[PDB]
Image 1 (tube, rainbow, N blue to C red):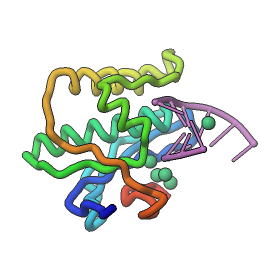
Image 2: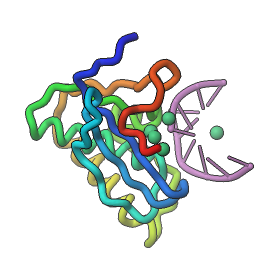
Image 3: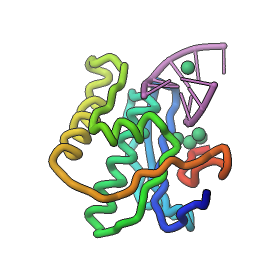
Length: 134
RNA sequence: ACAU
DNA sequence: CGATGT
Ligand SMILES: [K+]
Ligand SMILES: [K+]
Ligand SMILES: [K+]
Ligand SMILES: [Mn+2]
Ligand SMILES: [Mn+2]
């Protein structure tokens, strides 16, 4: 119904899918960029969306913030809930980096706790998420 | 079909 | 038009 403005919004950007992947997190209210991941040479849209949420969780936990996280990715929200990124991307030398980060994100989820609500950004009602790359 |  | 996902 209503946007929870006191929140963090995350999004992925890519050049190709699979292709170069990056992500960032922004204050939903102001658009201030709070974190930005250095581009990863080969990844998928969904792996980046997943890494972005998990980074948000870690960022908010480190700062003792109870703000929710918005993502527009049905897929990544489910992968975080499951603590398992069910990506189809081949594992090889050129995808080793993204797969390491994904494995490490799953590992963090399996060894830490959080109460952070992970919320679907309702693009059809609200427009593009504030972290979008345009 | 829906989410990207 | 292509791809990643539930
Ligand atoms: K964009
Ligand atoms: K979108
Ligand atoms: K499809
Ligand atoms: Mn997105
Ligand atoms: Mn976007």
